[PDB]
Image 1 (cartoon, rainbow, N blue to C red):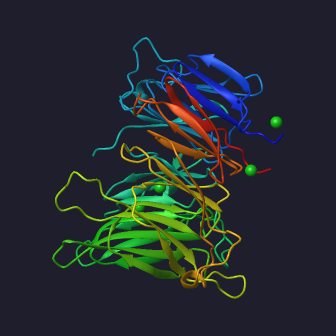
Image 2: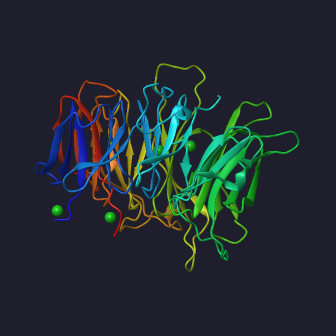
Image 3: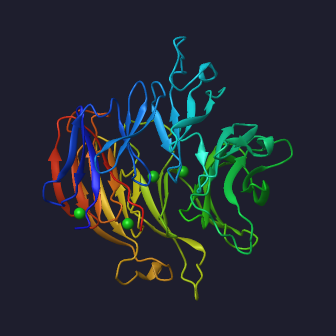
Length: 460
Ligand SMILES: [Cl-]
Ligand SMILES: [Cl-]
Ligand SMILES: [Cl-]
Ligand SMILES: [Cl-]
């Protein structure tokens, strides 16, 4: 059938189900109190993760039997390395080790919040305490599970090499003023580089007589392969493309008056010689959403103007598409504005994992629930003003879901699930099942629907 599994957690019961489109989901399993607080899928779909006060547990196999156990007390957040080789557990409450003894941890782990585990052996590799002075993950992974890093804001970036979890060159990367950083989501083959490397971007604000900058570092050489100096900058956001082909930096800027001014989008061509940087566009309003097309070269933003009165009426939002120009040959033209939609309340972007199709949504709002299903490679005639661009934008269908909180695409990019979680509000928990086109296949009301989550499937 080529169906996909998914999990739903309602009340105190969680179950793995087959997908039957409009027909009722076939149930592989259902259990009561499988988890205490939440349920999370392993990124390659191998494990189902349950969380308890004592520990976090990994369920899997045809039997759906226990596979691994990680005795971290009172975990709130859990993350995996991209290749499922390692596990990261976090607790807001610092670990308290009993004098009686802990079956795995020791006094060295007391007062700490993070633990990094080796899944295969279930043994803890390192323990870390909370930083001096919400976001997740904090420990960020390289694409190949070889490096994991944490930001020491204003000072350095501590990079560790696995499986030993040893500090690289017995030193943290000194970067004065470093505000944030992101690894590339893939192992990038830059042109002409024969050596192994992993890439991450970072940024610093203005320091003394040096301007604010965005950097691109190669690990483990720790060489900076490209710097980009920026001016009049309020804040910087760094957005990697899925293959690591492109890196877009969003820059919040200001006037000499230091009033809010404009936002600039600039793009790195990471694979190309010299690492060229291009100035895409400068936009007046603030950006509240940004999303690259997975495995593609298209991205969407959602903007909203600045409020002066903090007025009762919600701000309307504008969604804009950007795509590269058509270019003769196996190359990609310069990034250009494609189209801006009419003002509306949208505030969420959900690209398909395949990346042709994107769902523009309106979630966590009481005034509107609208859903839009768009195609970027529609078999149609491009309008005159958008004719040179490498895209054919077309609305494939609309939909709605009252009190919607979340949406998730299926791995195959054929189905879109939306749901109202009990975690945010209890008024009308439900899940909708759509296809890519936006046709409502089925919906269902569950009294205490906590979460839907597709089971990830890596391409064979
Ligand atoms: Cl099947
Ligand atoms: Cl952003
Ligand atoms: Cl987003
Ligand atoms: Cl697939």
